[PDB]
Image 1: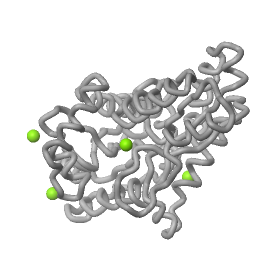
Image 2: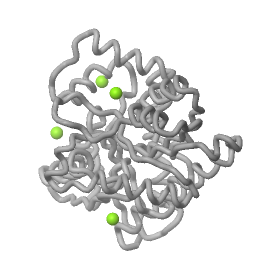
Image 3: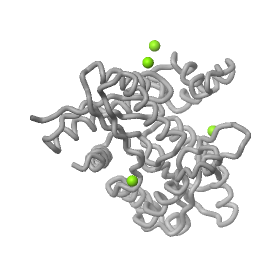
Length: 309
Ligand SMILES: [Mg+2]
Ligand SMILES: [Mg+2]
Ligand SMILES: [Mg+2]
Ligand SMILES: [Mg+2]
């Protein structure tokens, strides 16, 4: 009766253990192994945020919770989740191969990044579908974006409202909300990539839903290829906006990220906090979705909507 489907949950990835950081970094660097000092600097960043070990566990918990919740809220499909990561084991291809081995013939995929981009989501979905094509007898339908799912917007609206209500009056009336996602090369716009437009729309939805009077859109975690990356960077944006108007509180909503990973714990909670401490402003960064029920329900709704169910 009740049919079985694979649930392919994809993400950029974080190593599960320190010994895999070098191979992760090499993958991200397109085969160029980091020099030893560069490797140690990355290791030191994971140490600085309390250790790498908790990070991969969040993605595990998200996939686990999403399977369980999807299987409780409807009876037509029994999902089995498989995690496929872009840059470290289990790779996207490994997950699809495991689905196929397990007898899955039909799967739905979702990327744990709400905005579509040609560099991330589209590439992950193509990798998944190419592996399925090689194995045969398995097809995948893929979610491309979900930033506009109302339950996801409401997660962030509610967290942002909570944070502003937490503030003393003078911060409330002199605060700036910075909404961000992972930078990519500006060149994606020459392929018509809507990624920046979707980040701006997330910011608009969240700011207006939360009743925030002043907000700005920034990017974080850019790379180092010489051609321009989407900007401004959140560190620069923070200072710039302070230099204009003297905000005494900054609230960071790294809406492009779904978990407490290095880009949030280091690039927001360390690098942006350095800047807010320097200028005398308070720092706030509301809880990331992680594996909390409200967020899992938002993702389950995304998946069921994709299937028309
Ligand atoms: Mg190994
Ligand atoms: Mg293979
Ligand atoms: Mg859509
Ligand atoms: Mg950086």
